Amino acid sequence: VEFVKICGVKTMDELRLVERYADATGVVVNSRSKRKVPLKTAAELIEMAEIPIYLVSTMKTFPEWANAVEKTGAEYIQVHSDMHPKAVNRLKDEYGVSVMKAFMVPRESDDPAEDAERLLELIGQYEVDKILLDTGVGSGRRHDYRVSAIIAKEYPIVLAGGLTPENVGEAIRWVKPAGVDVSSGVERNGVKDRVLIEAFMAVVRNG
Ligand code: NA
Ligand code: NA
């Protein structure tokens, strides 16, 4: 019925773990991230993966992406930058990658419906396999949930940012997204952790 991604694996151990639970995972490259790995290391993880594994990056220009895809043999990419729809399509046509495009939830301003219309317009510029909404922190988070809830009615989105076993349940029947993306919420000491993932999954696994 749904889609769970566990993002930001850095080792084979972490990867084989998430594959027991998640519908997809991700390896971060060329980004500002505690989870960044070098391209070669990403390549090795991508080679052994049994589920979809996204090449996750904030890379902004096509050659950067083209080169990363070439070195990793990624079949999936998560585009976590405002890269032009045409550049995305180029990567799709020239490399056969499937794309999840990440969108920051805009907070400014000030009614959730207005940011949602600004985001819907932005989303509709893209021709991509999946849409990921990256929610933020602070009290502005409930605003992000409402924005995301509007969006999730027009597209089967993947809800992301700040999800934990303790808050994902609320997140889900608030936004009712098609999927959820989790990274640090299932890490014990920066390592993908089984009991946390199971606890996270236990909340998801109800429909
Ligand atoms: Na293990
Ligand atoms: Na088990």
Image (cartoon, rainbow, N blue to C red):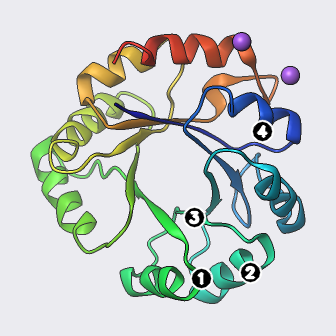
Judged from the image, the secondary structure of the residue bearing numbered disc 1 is: helix
Q: Residues within 10 Å of mark 4 (few under 14, many from 20)?
A: many
Crowd tier of the residue under label 1, counting other residues whose Cα lies within 10 Å: few below 14, some 14–19, many 20 or above: some
Q: Quadrant of ligand 2?
A: top right
Residue 111 position, x and y percent, is: 12, 43
Residue occupying the point 22% across, 42% down: 152
Pointer 1 and pointer 2: residues touching (CB < 8 Å)?
A: yes
Q: Amino acid at mark 1?
A: Tyr
4 and 1 marks in contact (CB < 8 Å): no
Above or below, 1 relative to 39: above
Labels 1 and 2: the sequence-earlier one = 2
Quadrant of the rendered image containing residue 197: top right
Give the foreground label among 3 and 1.
Answer: 1
SS assignment at label 3:
strand
Name the quadrant containing residue 94: bottom right
- Considering the numbered disc 2 on the image, is that residue within a helix, a strand or a loop? helix
- Residue 202, position in %: x, y? 51, 10
Question: Residue type at mark 2?
Answer: Glu
Determine which of the numbered discs, if any, sits on residue 29 in the image.
Answer: none
Q: Looking at the figure, which quarter contains the C terminus?
A: top left
Q: What residue sits right under mark 3 in the picture?
A: 77
Please report whichever mark, 3 or 2, sits nearer to the chain's N-terminal start.
2
Residue 165 locus on image (x, y percent)? 53, 15
Circle 2 residue: 70
